[PDB]
Length: 22
Length: 31
Image (cartoon, rainbow over all chains, first blue to last red; front, side):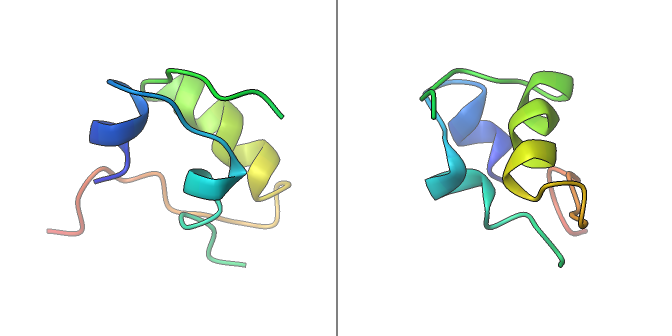
């Protein structure tokens, strides 16, 4: 899960735009 | 854009901006 990376470390569109379904 | 630590609702606060309310699945695991 991306949460395991974003909640412990640091995230931006470069990580989060992988969640989008649209 | 800011590189930041985010859990759940904060992580969706980036997700919702990154996906621009078009749509997403914030679920931590598929199954």
